[PDB]
Length: 294
Image (cartoon, rainbow, N blue to C red; front, side, top):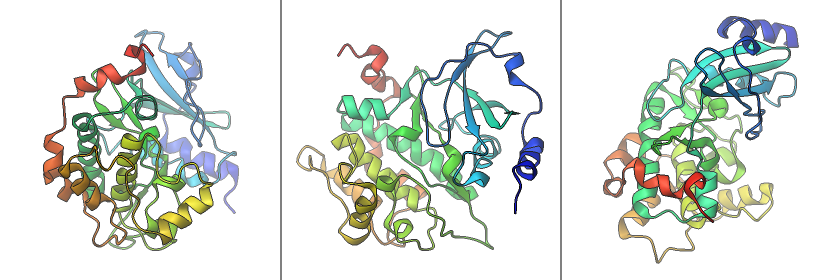
């Protein structure tokens, strides 16, 4: 029996108090996640562009996850993680004022264009460098996908949408809770078992299929049957298994391991040769819609 009020009071302390509508003006909606809207605003004083994630407290499936965002954006800061400026509380909504990422989402790049290996390797590297820090401090970002990955004007990768991450300790080292995007889920999570931080390594594997094949495995299928197939059947494979290098296939084989105990860790993968192909963040800039002619 956690009242809507008792909850608000819990956030009232962890957030920046006051009304952010005081110093922000140019509110226009850019996109929409499962949690809420990512409406972008302009500052009055600086005159700079910032993203403002509004999320309703009442309209939530798992309400106590709202903490994840802000609680990870701070205490877990990094070059390949999004920067949060502030976080306020308004009416019945949670407003998180964040850095504006000019490059946009990865979803756009993979669907419309085909990335070469040197670009794909750069993205995987940046994510692992972010994960290796999170996993080491005991964090599981349980919703890894192209939709959660944002890019800068440089093309520098930034992991985002932390709402679906989880904390683990020596007391509670694993979790059962079912969280993430059906298609990018690891089997042990789909099966509703104790899952450690290796769920993200499978999910990163599914993103590599998304990066190559444009969409993830069994995507055209319904959501419930897609999971049954990932859980029951063999590790999913690429359609373009002929175009990929010997290195990439060998890399992805360590990501898409069904048995979590056998599936590679974050630290392990950083040493893998494939990530030597990783091209400069500037090599992603041409593939960004802004510069795409169509």
